[PDB]
Length: 350
Ligand SMILES: NC1=Nc2nc3cc4c(cc3n2[C@H](c2ccc(OCc3cn5ccccc5n3)cc2)N1)OCCCO4
Image (cartoon, rainbow, N blue to C red; front, side):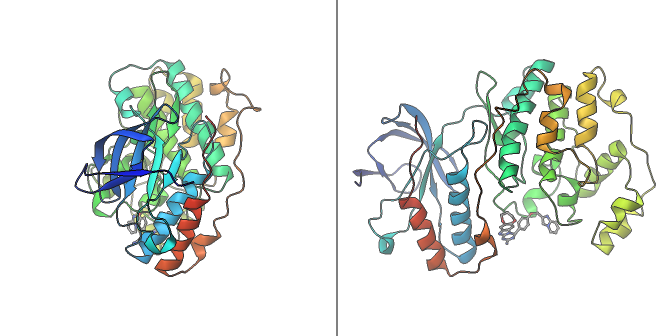
C-alpha cells in the first residue's frame, strides 16, 4: 500500500517524501542530486535521503540512474553501503519523474581520522581489513569501485567502516586536473589510460590509503598527472619490457620509455618504523603490473591481518547481472526499467 507523502521546500526544490521520514535538513547538493538528513520514524535510524537531479534528462543520465539503483539494490554486506529504501511519489509509470534513495546517515569519513589521531598499527590493521573484506565481496560480483579514496570510506566511533559512493562513471577531466585528491589514489593504468583495467585498480587505491594511514601523509600527491607518475615510478621503479608490452597506447609506451630507468626503492626505508608485515603487504599491493598485484581475497590471508582474518566470515556476493551495460536503449526504456526496480524493492531486515 502506498504511504502518504507530504511536501516541503528545503533546498531550492520541492521534496515529496513518505510521512515516516521526519526532520529533513539539507546537508549537501551537487549536479548529481540534493541530499537531506532525516529521521526514519519507522526504523529509528538517522538516514540520508538523496533526490536525484534530472534522473532521465538524457540516455546517458537515464542509464546512470538505472545503474546506480541496480548497484545499491545488490549490495548486502557489513562493509558496503546498502539501500534502506527507494521511493517515488508517482502513482504510475506515466507520471514517474523523481527518484529518492535512502541510506544510512554516515558521519565521519577516513579523512576525519587520518589528521587527528596518530592511529595505532592495530587501528590500521582493522581499518584496512574491513576495506579488503568489503572489496572481496564487491569484486566477487565483478564490480569495480574505481574511485576508492578516504572520503568514500565512512568510519563510526567504533572504527567500523563502510565503502561508499561507487565510481559510476563521471569525474570530468577538469575535476581530475592539478593538485587534487580526486587523482592521488588512482592506479597509473587508469590515470593515463594505459590499458583495459581490472579490479586490481582498487587494490592500488587501498595501498595508497594504507600508506597514508601509516605516515599521516599522502603517498603520491602529484601536482598533475605527469608529476604524479614520476612520484609513483620513483617508489616502485620504472616498468620493464614485460609490462611495457601490455600498454596498448603506442604513444603512452613511447613516453614511458623517455624516462630514465629507476629501481624499486626499499620500502622499509620509506615507511620508517612500520610493522615489517605492513611493509610486505604494501610491496604486494603497490605493484605497477596489475596482473601481479595481490587480490583482495589473497590479502585477507596475509599475516598482517592474522588477528582479524576469519575465512568463514568473509562472504562473497550473489551473482550480479550486468548485461545491461552492453545494451543500447531509449530514455523511456531505461526509465521503465528503473521504475520496475523501484516498485520491486524489498526493505532489509533491521
Ligand atoms: N561522457 C561519458 N559518459 C560515461 N558513462 C559511463 C559508464 C561506465 C563507465 C564510463 C562511462 N562514461 C565516460 C567516462 C568515464 C570516466 C572517465 O574518467 C577517467 C579518464 C578517461 N580519460 C581519457 C583520456 C585522458 C584522461 C582520462 N581520464 C572518463 C570518461 N564518458 O565505465 C564504468 C563505470 C560505469 O560504466
